[PDB]
Image (cartoon, rainbow, N blue to C red):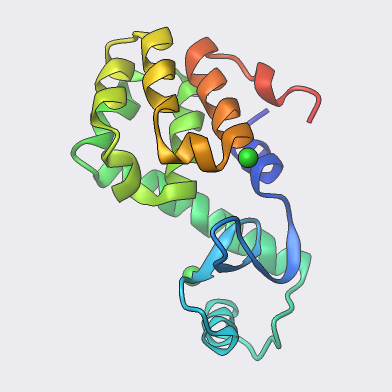
Length: 164
Ligand SMILES: [Cl-]
Ligand SMILES: [Cl-]
């Protein structure tokens, strides 16, 4: 198991524009297009991202390419973030993947706001951090996915993703 496989399980793969859990236009493997309520705005962002007139539909290769870019961007945002970087450096390989997952889903800013959980993770207080992470809108709105990430942080293994 690795970050790519992990996120592919959490986000799924859709080749036509769709609305995510928050109702935002998205495509591929969780690639957010726009928070705007307009399909046109979404189609236009898609074309700009792919480099062609797509008509709201892309191929698998195109989806994977956006995915690669997005993971890279997520890692780069963590490393550039003063609050995130120290946490990430302190963690093992499996838990790093869970932090990337969260950044991919909610953005650097969002994650950087979990101050208390971040400090617990850096301290290696696994159970405590897991309880604190669950007290969030994130867990209440997408509980199954949040549970998977939280279990990951708690155990340092891929058990939550094994079977999926
Ligand atoms: Cl892009
Ligand atoms: Cl969920």
